[PDB]
Image (cartoon, coloured by chain):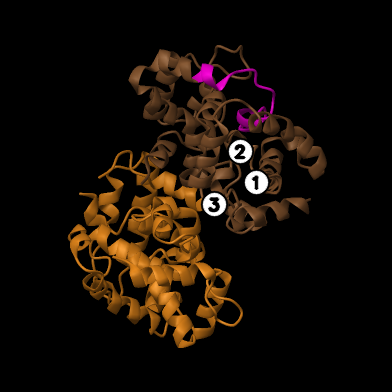
Chain colours: A brown, B orange
Amino acid sequence: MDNYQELAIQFAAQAVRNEIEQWVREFAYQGFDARRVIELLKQYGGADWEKDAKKMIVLALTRGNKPRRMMMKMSKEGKATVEALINKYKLKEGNPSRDELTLSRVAAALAGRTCQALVVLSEWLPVTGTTMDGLSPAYPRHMMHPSFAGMVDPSLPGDYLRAILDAHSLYLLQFSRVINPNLRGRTKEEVAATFTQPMNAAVNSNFISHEKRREFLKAFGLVDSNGKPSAAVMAAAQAYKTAA
Amino acid sequence: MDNYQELAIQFAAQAVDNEIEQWVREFAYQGFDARRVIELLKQYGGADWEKDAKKMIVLALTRGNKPRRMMMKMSKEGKATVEALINKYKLKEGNPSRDELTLSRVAAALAGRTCQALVVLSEWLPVTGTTMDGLSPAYPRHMMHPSFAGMVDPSLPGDYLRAILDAHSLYLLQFSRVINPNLRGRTKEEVAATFTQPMNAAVNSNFISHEKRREFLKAFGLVDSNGKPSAAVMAAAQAYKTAA
């Protein structure tokens, strides 16, 4: 199997409790620079920073943003690996100062890697690809994480951009209601008020150029060489226009 | 997550296995009535037979056809579950006599359940959905097991029928090459000779009606109300026609 999945298995809980603690803060403001995250990873990790970052991406996508808590129900190998990560990278929780690493900051700084992992880790996420397919056929797995907004090129023609973000907002809507039970009984407009802000921030950040971002979107199958969105993105976008 | 995945996790090896041997003999002749298999499941399993069958499908798809061997590297919880299955169902390996159960026969006799499970278990299989997507985009997950042949309605219009079996044959070509690596360097038609006869036997067997099979194919999204294959089936059939 793909090594992303091998890692997901190493880090799975023996059973499921206070799971909601792991995800509830996902759209809470984060004050950091992606460049600084990468510097800190290299500084603490040496040449193995990339291998270690991969483990942290699996943790962020499949278990949450609280490394110490997620160790509690892990296998012995799992716990050991996570404890070594915490100690090497000095991992924190929540929204620490700007020179600290968290699992979510790592996932977000390596957005290109994170989103490519979503193709393999689809059935391990809070909202699965199968669940998204019920809302729109062939939903793009590369969109199934908040860090995807950092892959969006804002210089795409306006109609192509709006489709990409609309398609992605379909997953954000679902994900938001799952991770935050306070939003389950709410309208799309009220839920969108909670995820549009950090979304638009990453869309317009200076981390990863327009050109590089668009290369990722083309490599992910989400746009063609003209920037025109795939039929699956188009179907997702319209599904979001009339979503409840 | 979906319960099929929770089961796959419970049954996962702590490390990889001589793993090839779990999967060899997949296309080896099988002398069983699927009706007899179901009779034996009901006799040994009683009212919980379907719940136990679910577990055995997960083992057959993700771990192989040798129950004693696959336990060796499982968790204590997994091992205990598989032990209780061996003793309750009297599970055998290889191609035993007609009144014996194996994990492969269970999967095949419950083809309709097995093929639906592939949607969730794609990334656990010896050939993953992501690998198939490399060969033809949006490759149908429901086709990704030899037991799919028992879901094919032979009364489909010849053209539609050929598209469904050509689409499914794209998977079998890949799968045969994973279980016998020597077939990687053999021509497509040489590899097809190793899988076509058992495929055709299942297509033409008397188990599950033309009508019920076509309903499954419609429920699986592989054909429409009139038997016409989906766009992704048609692309996979064409890919098989050009495949190495």
| Image-quadrant location for residue A138 | bottom right
On the image, numbered disc 2 is attached to which residue?
A152
How many C-alpha atoms fall within 10 Å of the one at disc 2: few (<14), some, or many (≥20)?
Answer: many
Distance from label 1 to label 2 (Cα)?
Answer: 8 Å
Considering only order in the chain, which callout, 3 or 2, is on the residue closer to the N terminus?
2
Nearer to the camera, B24 or B238? B238
Q: What kind of residue is marked 2?
A: Val
Considering only order in the chain, which callout, 2 or 1, is on the residue closer to the N terminus?
2
How many C-alpha atoms fall within 10 Å of the one at disc 1: few (<14), some, or many (≥20)?
Answer: many
Q: Are marks 1 and 2 in contact (CB under 8 Å)?
A: yes
Tags 1 and 2 on a common chain = yes
Image x and y of residue A29, in percent = 69, 23
What chain is tagged by disc 2? A
Image point (65%, 21%), residue name? A30
Tag in front: 1 or 3:
3
On the image, numbered disc 1 is attached to which residue?
A164
For residue B163, above or below residue A89: below
On the image, numbered disc 3 is attached to which residue?
A224
Distance from label 1 to label 3 (Cα)?
Answer: 12 Å
| Image-quadrant location for residue B28 | bottom left
Could you say whether the residue bearing mark 1 is in a helix, strand or loop? helix
Nearer to the camera, B139 or B32? B139
Image x and y of residue B68, in percent = 26, 52
Q: What kind of residue is marked 1?
A: Ile
How many C-alpha atoms fall within 10 Å of the one at disc 3: few (<14), some, or many (≥20)?
Answer: some
On the question of residue B161 being in view, the answer is yes
In the image, taking residue A183 as reference, residue B144 lies left or right, namely left
Considering only order in the chain, which callout, 3 or 1, is on the residue closer to the N terminus?
1
Extent of the magenta region: A17-37
